[PDB]
Image (cartoon, grey):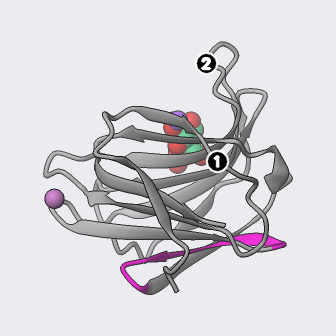
Amino acid sequence: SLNNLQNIIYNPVIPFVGTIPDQLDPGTLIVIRGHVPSDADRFQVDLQNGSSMKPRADVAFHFNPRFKRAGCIVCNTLINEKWGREEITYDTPFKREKSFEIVIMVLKDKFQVAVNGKHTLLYGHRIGPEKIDTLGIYGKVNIHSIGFSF
Ligand SMILES: OC[C@H]1O[C@@H](O[C@H]2[C@H](O)[C@@H](O)[C@H](O)O[C@@H]2CO)[C@H](O)[C@@H](O)[C@H]1O
Ligand code: NA
Ligand code: NI
């Protein structure tokens, strides 16, 4: 249910980096609506510990749709500017020139991600979700809205 969803941020310029307005406790939703442009090779939604660039902030949850060949979604965690073990989901619901609604649900033990009303993937927590205070969106993607349900 998307009641309690409050959209902030409309049509942000990409790259977008913004502070998350509350702690990502179990039951929290992050809802991102947009489109993949026709020339898209990849984009990413990063749940970050801070917004530092040098050194690069840790990414607790890197959610990275890629579109070359059959496409996929790579999920991973960045710590001390080093990527961890990749979790690759090959059944991607993203397609160039198609719209999407990403819903990231924060559970106690994992993120549960649904795209356009259909379950997409799970990703177990590698960093405590309380350390997540920043949402980054990078790459070839168009964003209409970003909202949260706490
Ligand atoms: O793990 C996410 C991370 O991947 C990097 O690229 C990987 C690539 O996904 C992997 O299949 C290949 O074998 O090695 C590369 C390691 O650099 C990206 O450069 C980075 O942006 C992240 O998306
Ligand atoms: Na990256
Ligand atoms: Ni549109």
Which amino acid type is shown beneath numbered disc 1? Pro
At 38% from the left edge and 46% from the top edge, which residue is drawn?
43
Foreground pick, 14 / 19: 19
Are circles 1 and 2 on residues that touch, CB within 8 Å?
A: no
Q: Residue at x 79, y 61 (%)?
A: 125
Instruction: Decide if residue 127 is in sight here.
Output: no
Residue 136 is situated, as x and y percent measured from the top left of the image, at 52, 40
Q: Does residue 78 appear in this view?
A: yes
Residue with the mark numbered 2: 53
Pointer 1 local density, CA inside 10 Å: few below 14, some 14–19, many at least 20 = few
Placement of 42 over or under 107, stated as above or below: above
In-front residue for pair 62/129: 129
* Element class at badge 2: loop
Query: Label 1, on which residue?
Result: 21
- Which is closer to the viewer, label 1 or label 2? 1
Q: Which residues are magenta?
A: 108-117
